[PDB]
Amino acid sequence: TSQVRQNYHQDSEAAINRQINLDLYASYVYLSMSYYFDRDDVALKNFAKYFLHQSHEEREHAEKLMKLQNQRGGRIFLQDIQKPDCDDWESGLNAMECALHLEKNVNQSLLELHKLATDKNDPHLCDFIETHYLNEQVKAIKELGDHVTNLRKMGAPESGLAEYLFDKHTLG
Amino acid sequence: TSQVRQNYHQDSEAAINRQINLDLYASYVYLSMSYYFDRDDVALKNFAKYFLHQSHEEREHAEKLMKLQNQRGGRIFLQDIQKPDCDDWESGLNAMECALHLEKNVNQSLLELHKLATDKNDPHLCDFIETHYLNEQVKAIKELGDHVTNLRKMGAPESGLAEYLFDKHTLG
Amino acid sequence: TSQVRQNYHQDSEAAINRQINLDLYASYVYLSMSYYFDRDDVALKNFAKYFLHQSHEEREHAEKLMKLQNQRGGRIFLQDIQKPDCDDWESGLNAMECALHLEKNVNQSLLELHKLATDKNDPHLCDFIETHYLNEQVKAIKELGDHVTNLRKMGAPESGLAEYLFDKHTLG
Amino acid sequence: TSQVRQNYHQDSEAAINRQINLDLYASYVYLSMSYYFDRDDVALKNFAKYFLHQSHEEREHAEKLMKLQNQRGGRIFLQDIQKPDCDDWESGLNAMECALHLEKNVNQSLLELHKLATDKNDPHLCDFIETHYLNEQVKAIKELGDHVTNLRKMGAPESGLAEYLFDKHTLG
Amino acid sequence: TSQVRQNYHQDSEAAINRQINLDLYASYVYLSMSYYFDRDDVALKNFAKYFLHQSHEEREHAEKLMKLQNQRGGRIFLQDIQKPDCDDWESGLNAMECALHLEKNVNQSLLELHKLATDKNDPHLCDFIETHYLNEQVKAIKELGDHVTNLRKMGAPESGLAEYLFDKHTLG
Amino acid sequence: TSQVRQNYHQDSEAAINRQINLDLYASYVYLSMSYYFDRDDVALKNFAKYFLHQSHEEREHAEKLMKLQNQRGGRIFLQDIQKPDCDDWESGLNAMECALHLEKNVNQSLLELHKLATDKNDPHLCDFIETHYLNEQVKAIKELGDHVTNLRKMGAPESGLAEYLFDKHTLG
Ligand SMILES: [Ca+2]
Ligand SMILES: [Ca+2]
Ligand SMILES: [Ca+2]
Ligand SMILES: [Ca+2]
Ligand SMILES: [Ca+2]
Ligand SMILES: [Ca+2]
Ligand SMILES: [Ca+2]
Ligand SMILES: [Ca+2]
Ligand SMILES: [Ca+2]
Ligand SMILES: [Ca+2]
Ligand SMILES: [Ca+2]
Ligand SMILES: [Ca+2]
Ligand SMILES: [Ca+2]
Ligand SMILES: [Ca+2]
Ligand SMILES: [Zn+2]
Ligand SMILES: [Zn+2]
Ligand SMILES: [Zn+2]
Ligand SMILES: [Zn+2]
Ligand SMILES: [Zn+2]
Ligand SMILES: [Zn+2]
Ligand SMILES: [Zn+2]
């Protein structure tokens, strides 16, 4: 047992390792999305930039969880980072829809982690999740919903003009 | 023989003179494209500016090759700069397509020059071409592909609105 | 075929995708090493910082290759990022030894890629690898050899004092 | 007919296209002269610089005429830019003599254009030529006469010392 | 075998040691030339300064090769630095001619080294030579050709006035 | 006889040429020592820096003697710069010991030169040696004695920790 460990259940430790993997996976999804928009036959530079920023943010989320693991005296166990489900993300609108689904999945995992921390009477872990993760997710989900709505209302994905203008006026 | 000449094959010297002409020709194509967009019945100022910048860049490419010729002790032999194949370039999209074709042709010539320099065991000439020309071409070709893609997706050439907005938001 | 593709062999395209995965894997190895040194029972903050910097650098290497893939009109195909071979990296000296082995493996892959690019008469790809990757590797390998030498001469891994002082005076 | 065209004779339009070619040709002559002085067996850097500046100026003259063509609703028709009559320009003095002859030829063409514009009662075109071209030519011709005189008085072309010192003290 | 050594042939290692000696020798030649012009019966201060700068540059070339040797895990083996072939360098023009010959000899050695590196499939060493040495030599050779040409055209070595004025106006 | 020569014995002139060679030799010894510490299996960067600084200083000593030779109307005669006696310098302590021996040898030569200048009633040469060389040597010898003492007291060469810490705290 770590000399620092206190009130940290093995189930919590395992759940944190799963969440580290999930955040790394989300980083990889967004990396894949970014460079899709960098293709010469897609060529939406601000979609590419937006998703690349998202990728780096998700990696930061994972690193903060790794720091948390060690702070609490848990032991980090890394797993493979699965390749994303898609190689081709179709359109700006489809990528945004996929991102919205991803962020809702990450939120679900975080809510399950918070329930576990509550069940194990770990108020430090509860606070960590609330403070650093839950409002971040609510904001991310709202932003992506807003993007999806605008792209749909403008006439995406069929209107390449809509995605072009959204790239310039919202993401640029 | 020049007092400076060393390891510089006559075939390389001749190929450099051909490339000087090709870069001057590309400068002239882009000059012609620029002022097409300056016509009162075309009137896309940022297309005009983009192509004029391209023209001056290609002239710089030629001047650097002229400098190289003299650095190696070769002798510059200039040829006529042929007028471009078109007087009227049709549309922004067509001009961009033509530019993409031109840059791919220039790249092909440069790759043939690099093969020649390799066959003649001229590592200085190989390096000169790699350093100053080959990645420049890859970037130019990628940029023009990106432009063509966006113009097509926006609905050019039929949508005069698309070309107008591209002129403002991408080239301006 | 991409509108930008020129002189880019399918074998090169595939090799670039393998190298993207290898650089992502190296990023993950270094991430794992970093947080090992962040453990309360290891507690070498400058080893942690050094490896975290390495991790971010390797991710940048991968992103530049992804950019290259698209520049040349190739298509990025991502694969799983395998978890590193170790969860516990033993000591500062052992981690440095492992890093040296990793960087030599990455270098070997890059040298094989350069041979392939040479065999396929792709001077742009050759130049890209020389310019951005090969001297980076030679420097990384030299730096890690230097670190290993100093740690060994100081009496690591048996001397926890040696690793402490190296952490402060070399990595800090 | 262009929506902007007013009081612009077809003969004037054609003469402007001829003058565009002549200014491009003069740019090319001066380009050729510049790099002659950049040869290792000539090696007069300030002669090279002087002629290169002249080359860029003549290109600017052509671009301003292209702008004029479009301003008046005429249509630009480009022709081949002929290679200069010489590959080797002999000496500083000979190049200056050749430049003086060239500038007098360009002036003659411009005076013929002004006569045409006068005959066609085109005061805007008359003013354009007077304002932007005729005093430019008188100054260029005077400067080149002055240079020729000094080079001759100093003992060029036979005195390589004279051309060396002129390069330093007048052109540098 | 060095822990850093990878893809570095023993022939390459030996050739690098020969090149280190050659660059040190060139440094010594230029040192000797510099102080010749510092003699009271020669007294060309800017020739002295020019050659002294050259001397320090050649020493830097050698130090960078020594660094390269160690970077690749090769072992530096120094040899005697031979005294130059001349004690008295005759005139500014003769020294410049001798320097031109020296730089062409150094270039030949570097081209042979590049051929060896190519034959041994050492792209890092090829790149190192191209990047740091080959264009440096082409520039040095061109500069010295230019100097020789000017000195000859001005009437050196017979005209002590020519060498005096060249010292002031070109080297000063 | 030089027009500047006055009270300068041929024996003094010859002794100055020997001293120029000795200072160049000392520069080469220190160059060799520097890059030994740059080896991946030695890896003491501040030892490397210290010896490289020493090398450049000794070269400056030689250049000042070359200047002196010419000031007095003597004629510089260069000799081969012998390679140092060692390729491998063993340890920081051994290199410092070798440097101390070298500086004492250089001092002995300078004291013999001063005796010669005294015997030849050359007070300018006596002053030159006192002013620029003798206290420089006393300081260099004292500094190297101090270094040797500290390295020995710390437990070098057997303690790689001692040499590591000396490198950081004294030479860094
Ligand atoms: Ca996010
Ligand atoms: Ca999988
Ligand atoms: Ca271009
Ligand atoms: Ca024609
Ligand atoms: Ca690295
Ligand atoms: Ca696995
Ligand atoms: Ca002019
Ligand atoms: Ca013709
Ligand atoms: Ca008027
Ligand atoms: Ca040089
Ligand atoms: Ca000898
Ligand atoms: Ca290269
Ligand atoms: Ca010293
Ligand atoms: Ca010897
Ligand atoms: Zn996240
Ligand atoms: Zn808008
Ligand atoms: Zn070009
Ligand atoms: Zn990497
Ligand atoms: Zn003109
Ligand atoms: Zn050199
Ligand atoms: Zn000394």
Image (cartoon, coloured by chain):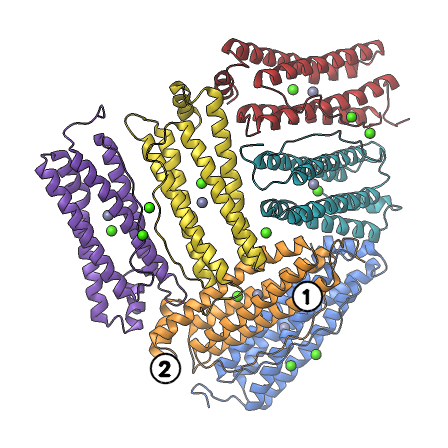
Chain colours: A purple, B orange, C yellow, D blue, E cyan, F red
- Which residue bears the numbered disc 1? B15
Q: Which quadrant holds the C terminus of chain A?
A: bottom left
Left-right relation of B142 to C118: left
Chain of the residue that carries numbered disc 1 in the rendered image: B
Residue B141 image position (x, y, % from top left)? 49, 66
Q: Is residue B167 visible?
A: no
- Which residue bears the numbered disc 2? B158
Q: Residue at x 43, y 76 (%)?
A: B93
Mark nearer the N terminus (2 vs 1): 1
Is residue B11 or residue F102 the one in the foreground? B11
Residue C104 image position (x, y, % from top left)? 49, 40
Amino acid type indicated by mark 2 = Glu
In the image, are marks 2 and 1 on the same chain? yes
- Residue sitting farthest toward the right: F1
**Image quarter for residue D149?**
bottom right
Chain of the residue that carries numbered disc 2 in the rendered image: B
Q: Is residue B105 above or below residue F101?
A: below
Amino acid type indicated by mark 1 = Ala
Is residue D102 or residue D118 the one in the foreground? D102
Residue C125 image position (x, y, % from top left)? 53, 56
Q: Is residue F18 above or below residue C127?
A: above
Residue D110 image position (x, y, % from top left)? 64, 80
